[PDB]
Length: 90
Length: 90
Ligand SMILES: [Mg+2]
Ligand SMILES: [Mg+2]
Ligand SMILES: [Mg+2]
Ligand SMILES: [Mg+2]
Ligand SMILES: [Mg+2]
Ligand SMILES: [Mg+2]
Ligand SMILES: [Mg+2]
Ligand SMILES: [Mg+2]
Ligand SMILES: [Mg+2]
Ligand SMILES: [Mg+2]
Image 1 (cartoon, rainbow over the protein chains, first blue to last red):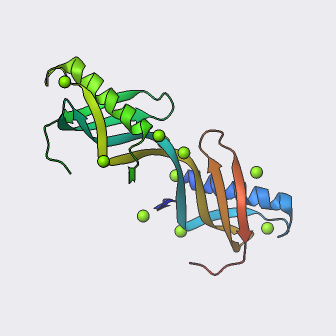
Image 2 (image 1 turned 90 degrees about the horizontal axis):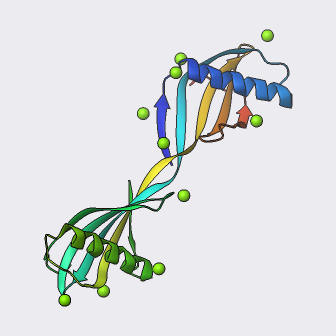
């Protein structure tokens, strides 16, 4: 769920050719001849999880610390981004 | 990105074990003994493009149509999601 307007260059003209080609196959609008795509062209991006970052409060040796951890979704590898303390309780 | 609060169950406790284990390797706070992860725990999600949807105004046979096209990022299959018209110029 992210939106934007994109320019109407060659990539967008190729999108219009595909749509007219596909509609000609369906036939519900006769035989159509592609002319051009005009402004505006709106584009939605659908996302998927690449990775994560966690911010923790962690007790260690009865003292409280802040830690940031990063995690890859595919390999599940983790990195310590930050570790400091003692910090006051939240 | 996108942010959320998560529960502090076994997955979050193991996040704290990782952070303390890694900090012990660095050594700046001496030898630390993991106790627990406490509230609150915040989680950020990093996103990658899964696919797209394009909303076009396209001239075909000198008539103006609205068309929506989807596009999968990895397999690159495109699909015609909608095609109607004539529509008034935007
Ligand atoms: Mg914009
Ligand atoms: Mg272009
Ligand atoms: Mg134009
Ligand atoms: Mg996902
Ligand atoms: Mg101890
Ligand atoms: Mg759990
Ligand atoms: Mg608690
Ligand atoms: Mg990407
Ligand atoms: Mg014609
Ligand atoms: Mg198709």
